[PDB]
Length: 239
Length: 239
Ligand SMILES: O=c1ccn([C@@H]2O[C@H](COP(=O)(O)OP(=O)(O)O)[C@@H](O)[C@H]2O)c(=O)[nH]1
Ligand SMILES: O=c1ccn([C@@H]2O[C@H](COP(=O)(O)OP(=O)(O)O)[C@@H](O)[C@H]2O)c(=O)[nH]1
Ligand SMILES: [Mn+2]
Ligand SMILES: [Mn+2]
Image (cartoon, rainbow over the protein chains, first blue to last red):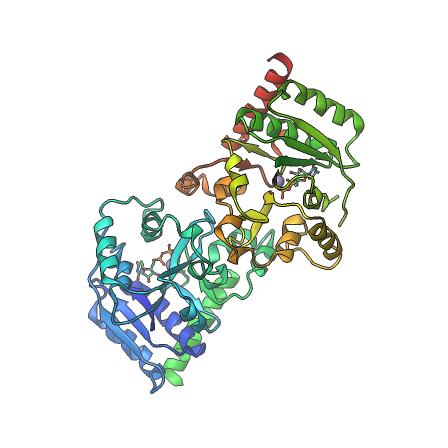
């Protein structure tokens, strides 16, 4: 079993670094695979590898894997379904950070789990996925990628069209929102109804969905991201 | 089995009237019980009864029931759990309208079903409830009403505290969002991402949550409510 993340542009390297360090800080008991697509330049890969080196130990491995871009690079994330050298993958977007150990996600008996999106709340968000790789399912995703329209023009819309009965699936396949707590809800509710956000307990993964990404541009959640990132740079370079 | 709605203030009488007529227009095959609490004046009850009279027939009955207010009248809705002269109740807020026949809701084998709220999407909204009445459960709701805090200060917060594992429950107990399509999502997404709202298919019950209520004060959904209400007044008085 492994955690996996994805980088398809040099500009997201700071997101990966914050995520890597948040997993290190949470003492996760499974290795991490960083997928990087063709558009990520080799110097950025080398920089990322150097940043991760001080977090490597005999008890935690961070590995790197080249993957081809999957165009609509908008579908490159589908590569997690082909990683069948692993029985189970916990995939996390590079614009998320882990606040608490989430190793229990590997205890879910399902081939596919995701957390609900906020709009609408009976569809799922594709930023956190717990999957069991299967190369035949991967092939059919690739094939259907040229047929199924996506209501958000991205991988979330496409995956919901491919798994339209996710909402009806068992509890193992539907992650609580605390495993993919999207800052878009915080932005909307914090000023008037902050109690809606405080209801999300435990809050284990923060997802910095929508734009700009925190490294691209001072809300409370963005302060938290920079706290994680700057500590990561401090510990990687000085620790 | 029956549909049920609730009025706890004279000012919501226009909401009840739009809802009653939307159920009539959808040709629902089960009767409707209108709960009215003590604060609703007798003349308003009489007006409502006269408005409903032309929709009464040998094949559809609208009945009225006095219920005592349940204070925190904020918990008066809990009275649906005591209606054990019915095996099953589909409860709908008076600020909703039915756009399509929803008689299939009575085919769900569960004691309690609700649709997800938008914030957060792993809690439920209490505006549409499919329940099997049970006077012992009612007693425990009343008892716990003096103990469990509500994260929104209302019945939705309280019922989520009472049923905190709703998200983990079976598909029968978790209604698709189309059975409680809250206009708050439309307000937020229509301008920028209208495709999120169009994903809600079928859209069977529109819930005019938040304020002001349409009869209290010209968005697209509010135009739709007034279309339903004004046709209802036309057919009740002229049809
Ligand atoms: O320019 C990009 C866009 C996407 N990604 C990767 O694809 C994931 C999904 O994209 P994104 O998080 O920006 O979408 P959102 O969550 O805002 O819908 C990102 O987290 C990254 O892992 C990336 O590396 N560079
Ligand atoms: O002043 C009121 C408040 C509530 N209600 C009844 O209680 C339900 C729930 O209240 P409301 O719909 O206003 O709450 P919201 O959906 O906006 O959270 C209403 O639909 C009515 O059935 C009412 O009759 N008068
Ligand atoms: Mn993301
Ligand atoms: Mn309501």
